[PDB]
Length: 96
Length: 7
Image (tube, rainbow over all chains, first blue to last red; front, side, top):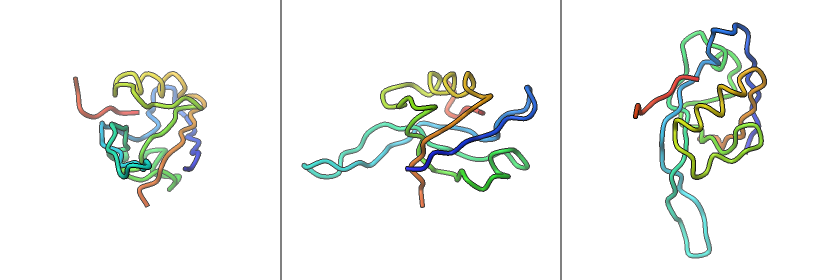
């Protein structure tokens, strides 16, 4: 896991990434068990997230500012992020 | 609902 801080410049400018629903493959004593998850689907060209080189397409979003997204909907998680947009920190599980 | 959300 990596904690990624995303800075915000314009009040009207987005942090520069899209999120989507996905499937997380996770490990349990039984074996690999699928679970719903939230992922970065793409980055805005020229945007803030891109420019950092810290977020990648298909990184899995694990937490928004310390709060796990497990069990939340895509809209709920979107609302968490934008609320926190001035000081957004996301814990990701990198695709690489 | 929409399948992608801009942040």
